[PDB]
Image (spheres, grey):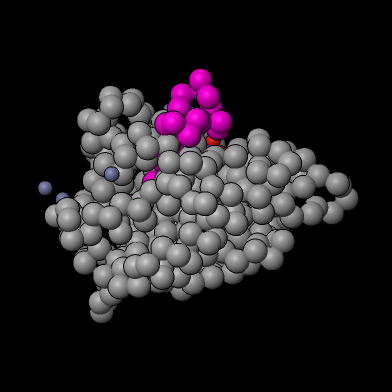
Amino acid sequence: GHSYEKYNNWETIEAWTKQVTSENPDLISRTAIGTTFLGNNIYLLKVGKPGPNKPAIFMDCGIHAREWISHAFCQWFVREAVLTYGYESHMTEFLNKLDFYVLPVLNIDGYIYTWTKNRMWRKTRSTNAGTTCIGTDPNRNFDAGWCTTGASTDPCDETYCGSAAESEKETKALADFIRNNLSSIKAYLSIHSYSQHIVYPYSYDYKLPENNAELNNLAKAAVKELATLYGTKYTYGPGATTLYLAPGGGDDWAYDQGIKYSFTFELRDKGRYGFILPESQIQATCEETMLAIKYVTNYVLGHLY
Ligand SMILES: NCCCC[C@H](NS(N)(=O)=O)C(=O)O
Ligand SMILES: [Zn+2]
Ligand SMILES: [Zn+2]
Ligand SMILES: [Zn+2]
Ligand SMILES: [Zn+2]
Ligand SMILES: [Zn+2]
């Protein structure tokens, strides 16, 4: 039984991706962009009213297994699109002019493991040579300043970069999709938790992006829009500056592919519950995040390239 106000297991999310597509065929199409290490299908939802030469925004959730609110947000975004299309001016304009490539759960194997064995699991579930230690951090596995300071060469570590850039089938599947659709993808959004942050490149090195002033002003405004609903306080800025060095990230990789608007959203909370954010907070977290996402979406539409 699926619920947008509850954390759903992979079996439930998978059945939901099929159901939401069948219930809304004129607004959603579903494809498998590859398979995980354990052979699970990596589903991707193309959300929007079909049309020729449409620009797109890519958004992923569940890169890190324990960040259950991120998986919940991708489902809420799709919920919003199907419920408010034709009922709300902005969402109607967004789905007519843009397509949203929503990847609800990238690290499916890790997510299954948080539900079955270890709630605090972060990485993939792939094996490593010369150790019984499992998994690679997908957010340290992209080919952008890969395995430098901020990523670990130790397979037993939470920030393990992997054997090579894109060693993970999940990472390769995401990277291959973006590369195959580079001409249409105008924005990249990666949903994570926690610490209430809106981060933009760079994280692989201490350097500011070409459009730093633009990204700083956009993140500032997105943070402001999010705060209007419940007064939730978000901080923002370049990754290495506001957070820490985190090389091999999807956001930095997407940015270096030419995707000018690249953001990582760290959702609720600030540490009280951490990754174990209660279900009672899903609605509030998702609704306020919607305001920041819609603001970024509206900006991208007014600044197409
Ligand atoms: N691509 C830069 C994103 C950095 C933040 C992210 N934070 S988290 N969700 O706590 O793991 C991470 O360390 O991968
Ligand atoms: Zn308006
Ligand atoms: Zn994360
Ligand atoms: Zn910070
Ligand atoms: Zn709503
Ligand atoms: Zn402008």
x and y percent of residue 112 in the render? 66, 50
Return the x and y of residue 184 as percentages of the image width and height: 33, 69
Q: Can you give x and y, in whole percent of width and height, for residue 32 in the image?
A: 54, 70
Determine whether, in the image, residue 249 is placed left or right of residue 126. Answer: left
Nearer-the-camera pick, 246 or 52: 52
Quarter assignment of residue 55: bottom left
Q: Residue furthest top?
A: 272
Boundaries of the magenta span: 258-281
Q: Residue furthest right?
A: 130
**Image: 73 above or below 302:** above
Percent across and percent down for residue 292 are: 29, 41
**Picture quarter with ligand 4:** top left
Identity of the residue drawn at 60% across and 66% down: 41
Q: Is residue 110 visible?
A: no
The residue lying toward the viewer, choosing from 60 and 142, is: 60
Any part of residue 93 in sight: yes
Q: Quadrant of residue 167?
A: bottom right
